[PDB]
Image (cartoon, rainbow, N blue to C red; front, side, top):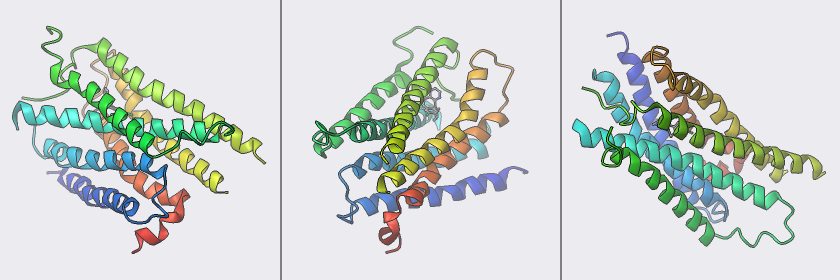
Length: 263
Ligand SMILES: Clc1ccc2c(c1)CCc1cccnc1C2=C1CCNCC1
């Protein structure tokens, strides 16, 4: 009776998130000058972003309006949320791989940046994401140990290991890549400058949005009586606000999106 208007606001977030994602997808599939050989990489993120919104928005809202469906639907919800997040933070990983390779002194380079390899690496990211999904459905039947939380919530060590891997290794390798990109930018004395700003703003938006979620998650990872239902919702939804913002963060630095966004 005192939290429903907030639920309505989070529901209103859905329309703009889905609209922005579909707008980016249509922009890529329309303009040849915008149909860049590398833009397809970021498209993966957008596609993942779109999935996120849908597969998370009503269901999680249906989690808030209701108090504490069945097993298959909620399990699929968790699995697809996990695959969407992993696919996003590996589309960004592929983007940083490609920026690192392309800005590294391109003498015997620029010949491994085609579109077939773009599709191949996107397919590989999707396949590895599904391989990460498989544990969500099959935590049981592999090991032998009303609400539907993560199935391995009672297992602290696996939780810590997966969080550590899927945050540190992407984010730390990404910071390495961004630092070397910035070093190359500084030594190479504007489109490259705006690409650097785009990568920097995407980095700032995750780090800032998913540092509270991860810090509180890792505090939970060793103690149970340390976070209620409140200090977690306000972090998950800042992260999803970040996912919504990324389609609008794209034109801020790479503003070639002018004509296609105002057709
Ligand atoms: Cl960068 C990032 C940030 C958060 C998460 C991931 C990736 C996926 C892996 C992962 C593993 C253990 C616990 N939580 C998660 C995350 C979730 C929970 C499900 N809903 C989406 C957010």
